[PDB]
Image (cartoon, rainbow, N blue to C red):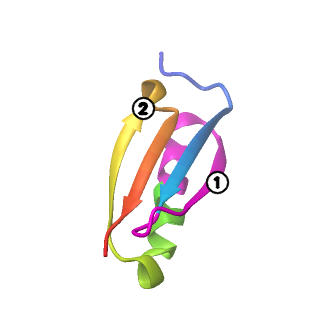
Amino acid sequence: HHAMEEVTIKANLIFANGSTQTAEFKGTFEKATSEAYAYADTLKKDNGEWTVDVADKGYTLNIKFAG
């Protein structure tokens, strides 16, 4: 039985120069997680490629952009 509660995935976006931005995605776990990464992807054009460190049991995504 997989978790079907509506949850919030927090994306802590960290840019190359150290600046940050936080966005959150609400929905079932995997759907919301995929949406968080999809959002990060829209920022690659101006911020470069990203890497991630998953925290808080998967509810926090620390996404760092390179460059």
Residue 33 on the magenta span: yes
Instruction: Name the side, left or right, on which 31 lies relative to 27.
Output: left
Q: Which residue is mark 1?
A: 23
Crowding at dot 1, Cα within 10 Å, few <14 / some 14-19 / many 20+, comes out as few
Q: Quadrant of residue 45?
A: bottom left
Please provide percent x and percent y for residue 23: 64, 54
- Tag shown at residue 4: none
Residue with the most extreme front position? 17
Dot 1 amino acid type: Ala
Work out whether mark 1 precedes mark 2 in sequence or the reverse, and give the earlier one: 1
Please provide percent x and percent y for residue 4: 60, 26
Crowding at dot 2, Cα within 10 Å, few <14 / some 14-19 / many 20+, comes out as few
Q: Which residue is mark 2?
A: 55
Q: What are the residue bounds of the magenta stretch? A: 15-36
Look at the picture and state if 8 lies above or below 64. Answer: above
- The residue lying at 34 percent from left, 42 percent from top is 53
Q: CA distance from mark 1 to mark 2?
A: 15 Å
Q: Secondary structure at mark 2?
A: strand
- The residue lying at 43 percent from left, 77 percent from top is 47
Please provide percent x and percent y for residue 14: 47, 58
Q: Secondary structure at mark 1?
A: strand
Residue 49 on the magenta span: no
- The residue lying at 46 percent from left, 83 percent from top is 46
Dot 2 amino acid type: Ala
